[PDB]
Amino acid sequence: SFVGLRVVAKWSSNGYFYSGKITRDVGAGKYKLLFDDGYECDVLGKDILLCDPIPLDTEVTALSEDEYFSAGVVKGHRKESGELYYSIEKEGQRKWYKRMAVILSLEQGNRLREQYGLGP
Ligand SMILES: CCN1CCN(C(=O)c2ccc(Cn3nc(C)cc3C)cc2)CC1
């Protein structure tokens, strides 16, 4: 019933949460995730945020094309040809970022667990 849903889920290697989809309930409190960057991983429910999109006014981390990142705040959403863009405000200035360029630090993801988390 969670299969096919979009999530933002913790990748254990760096502790950031990345965009992906639940592809399977694999039991033992874990789901098979397909991350948008092509990584298939089994992830604990407690590490999966069922938010699609990440809400307005959330503090997030956004990547540029050259892999530079910094914190910002979600100030908008836009759908184009089935794809989602986020308007992220950094130092008072906004740019549009594709879904998979918006990630959460461990602290930023932790903040959404109570409302959007799976498992416990
Ligand atoms: C979801 C799976 N996918 C898998 C591919 N990814 C990476 O190989 C990856 C690993 C480390 C970094 C560097 N970084 N960036 C931040 C921020 C924090 C840290 C330590 C960057 C990228 C990204 C994640």
Image: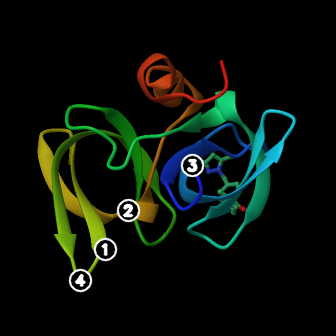
Q: Farthest residue in the front direction?
A: 1
Lower position in the chain sequence, tag 4 or tag 2: 4
Tag 1 residue: 83
Q: Do tag 4 and tag 1 residues touch (Cβ < 8 Å)?
A: yes
Of discs 2 and 1, which sits in the foreground? 1
Secondary structure found at label 4 = loop
Secondary structure found at label 3 = loop
**Screen quadrant of the C terminus:** top right
Between the C-alphas of marks 3 and 2, the distance is 20 Å
Residue 91: numbered disc: none
Task: Sort mark 1 into few (<14), some (14-19) or many (20+) by Cα contacts within 10 Å.
Answer: few
In the image, residue 55 lies at what x, y percent? 27, 38
Tag 4 residue: 81
Q: Do tag 2 and tag 1 residues touch (Cβ < 8 Å)?
A: yes
Q: Residue 27 falls in which quadrant of the image?
A: top right
Tag 2 residue: 99
Between the C-alphas of marks 2 and 1, the distance is 8 Å
